[PDB]
Amino acid sequence: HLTMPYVMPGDGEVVGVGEPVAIRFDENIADRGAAEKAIKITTNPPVEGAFYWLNNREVRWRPEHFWKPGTAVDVAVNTYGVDLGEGMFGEDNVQTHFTIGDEVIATADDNTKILTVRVNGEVVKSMPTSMGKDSTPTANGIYIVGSRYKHIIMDSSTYGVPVNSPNGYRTDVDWATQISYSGVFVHSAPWSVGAQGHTNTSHGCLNVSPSNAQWFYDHVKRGDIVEVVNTVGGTLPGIDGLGDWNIPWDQWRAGNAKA
């Protein structure tokens, strides 16, 4: 009846302007309020933020707007010996200090079929893209950048979907940057360079050229932002794991501690 917290980002990391503080427990938290009260976040420059639970084990904290570049963040998870409900006690404290890096926002516009990368407001790259075909479109919304992979075998069975079934797929890809836990990536697609900038051909991922995908892998980092606009899709779920910013601030701030 002990639970161990884990905090991200890790100590000393530099992350993009979309990165939430994440506190992950290894057991379901019965009294969410008790956990929230044990977690104090210091910011410099100071900014308001709030907690919102992504699931029963993980709470996120973020501001109303993307973080200001250069902000220094200290997280004190003072859970040692704290009663988290149903006789479950925190096993340890954890702490972290991290910093917000440059503002990096990449916008994929389905009306132009270009993915434009802006760093502190300035265009540094314009990449033709091919996104989800109309039957399997890319959702609009705000995506937080996660992990990156030099090579990945994308296999829909990872997500419980058989490869030889309607929503299945299996594709070996290079230079993949993850933008959702549901399996959306920016990646290399040499076979669709003709279509990039013209027609959508994918299952939902953002296909770009090999040199552009490698550039993206090299220069876009965890916590940077991808915004998709003007597609025929829906909106990325707020509780994806990297979809936090699709929950409006009024709802996020109200929280879900009594749920």
Image (cartoon, rainbow, N blue to C red):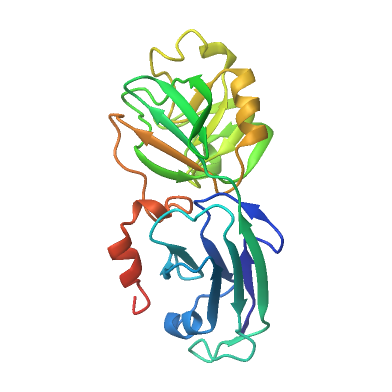
Left or right of 174, for residue 252: left
Residue 173 can be seen in this image: no
Classify 63 as above or below 143: below
Identify which residue, 256 or 77, lies in the foreground. Answer: 77
Residue 91 place in picture, x, y as percent: 66, 84
Image quadrant in which you'd find residue 257: bottom left
Residue 142 place in picture, x, y as percent: 40, 44
Residue 219 can be seen in this image: yes
Identify which residue, 129 or 63, lies in the foreground. Answer: 63
Q: Quadrant of the N terminus?
A: bottom right
Q: Residue at x 34, y 56 (%)?
A: 247
Residue 230 place in picture, x, y as percent: 29, 30
Residue 184 place in picture, x, y as percent: 49, 37
Q: Residue at x 39, y 53 (%)?
A: 245
Count of picture labels: 0
Q: Residue at x 43, y 68 (%)?
A: 49
Classify 176 as above or below 47: above
Q: Residue at x 51, y 41 (%)?
A: 179
Image quadrant in which you'd find residue 157: top right
